[PDB]
Length: 223
Image (cartoon, rainbow, N blue to C red):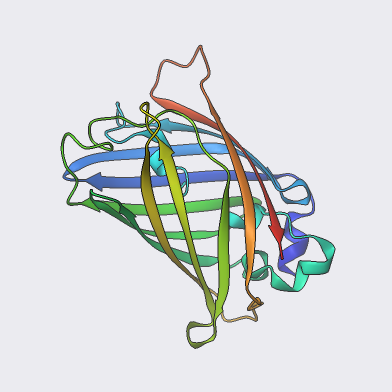
């Protein structure tokens, strides 16, 4: 059963290939998830050299199966219900006054390792805007992620807004439109409307010379 795969600490591997305004890059990530505590620890490395977009703009793209669902809300956890076969996660991320990311990922088990395998395409970015001109602070706010059932597609629709802080006190809005559908045949839980409360801490390994991001995340389901 899907939820039983997450009762302990689960190794995580993330692999992203990106192209934003023709700037190609790849990111690999390793760490672990403890869904009992809603906890994720991951270190991401840009394997192609310098990341051509700010690290924070990738956080949402780079495993909502690691959310903590309280006991009373267990019947609303789509993400674990689809495992081990997994789900497809697709998004469009509209950066206000700027370009968009379109992403397709498969989140599934490969042996004991939970894998997030992603392709990302960014288009219509301004070369001196907040994204390509690297004007976003290396930090991350706490958000509510709003989940609803999509019966027609046997999955979920997810919508939320990320606010990336800029030095002058303004924000770069990143409007997220998301859908998840199962990879496998088997039964999945289609939830009633609810949200995930998220928080993320970004940091650096002072002795890592590669372009990278260390991430600590806690996510709990509510309502």
